[PDB]
Image (cartoon, rainbow over all chains, first blue to last red; front, side):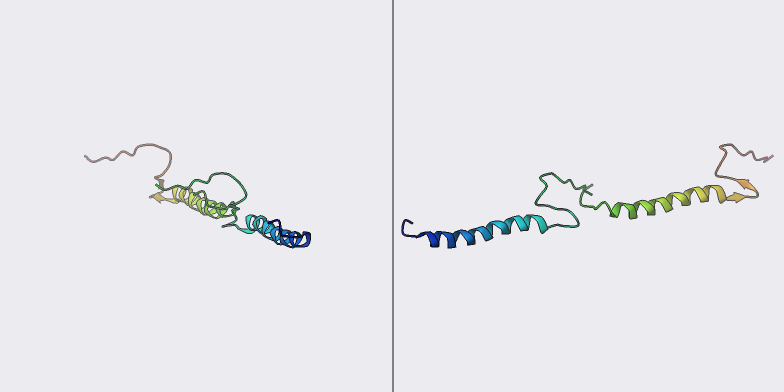
Length: 49
Length: 49
């Protein structure tokens, strides 16, 4: 909106900054049996049979 | 399975090691009347007449 002033824009941008860093955190800590699942970009194959 | 950790495989491996040793000991410890039966690849005549 064209209504806002400068301070309001800054006060929005900081909250945006927090949520941005949150995703980066979540990608790193999550892990299953010593396997990082959201930071590798490869394929894992089970055996059934 | 593809969801196993590098640590686990040694447990399975050393169990396998123990089992493999058992076969050899049974091979070389069994005997009948002083004749080892599970070695040397021969045949054993019997006089029956």
